[PDB]
Image (spheres, coloured by chain):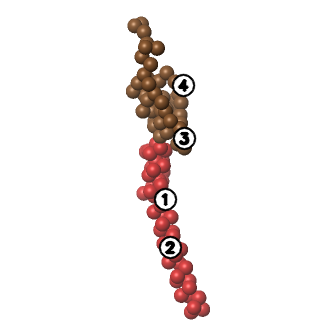
Amino acid sequence: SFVIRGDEVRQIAPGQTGKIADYNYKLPDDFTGCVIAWNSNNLDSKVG
Amino acid sequence: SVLNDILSRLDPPEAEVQIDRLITGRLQSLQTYVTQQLIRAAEIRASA
């Protein structure tokens, strides 16, 4: 389960490279599975 | 044409695809060489 930013989602995929993919979580090339993302705007976002 | 440059310049996710092309070619070439090699050897054997 991740909190990842919106633009970043492209990164959670087998091949990608970027801050999230490099520094935080990396999939193997061989990854077998799905990535289900949905913006949870209401749950975690505040005026501050 | 150089293996190192692909590794150097390209990320592995991209590199893997590129090297793969290079691999099939040489492997094909060696395959052509051995096949070519076998026939000539046979020619030699009959002569021998």
Q: Which residue is mark 1?
A: B23
Gap between marks 2 and 1 measured at Cα: 15 Å
Q: Are marks 4 and 2 on the same chain?
A: no
Q: Amino acid at mark 2?
A: Tyr
Under circle 3, the secondary element is: loop
- The chain identifier of the residue carrying mark 3 reads A
- Tell me, for residue A26, which label it has, or none: none
Amino acid type, label 1: Ile
Instruction: Please tell me which residue is depicted at 48% across the width and 66% down the height of the picture.
Output: B28
Q: Badge 4 is on which residue? A: A1
Circle 1: element type: helix
Cα separation, mark 4 vs mark 2, equals 52 Å
Residue A44 rendering spot, x and y as whole percentages: 46, 14
Asked whether the residues under marks 2 and 3 belong to the same chain, the reply is: no
Depth check, front residue: B40 or A43 = A43
Rendered hue of chain A is brown
Q: Which residue is label 3 attached to?
A: A32
Label 1: few (<14), some (14–19) or many (≥20) C-alpha neighbours in 10 Å: few
Work out whether A42 lies above or below A23. Answer: above
Under tag 2, what secondary structure? helix
Alpha carbons under labels 2 and 3: distance apart = 38 Å
Tell which subunit mark 2 falls on. B
**Residues marked 1 and 3 touching at CB (< 8 Å):** no
The residue that appears at 50% across and 64% down in the rendered structure is B27
Mark 4: few/some/many CA within 10 Å (<14, 14-19, 20+): few
Q: Position of residue A45 (x, y in %)?
A: 43, 13
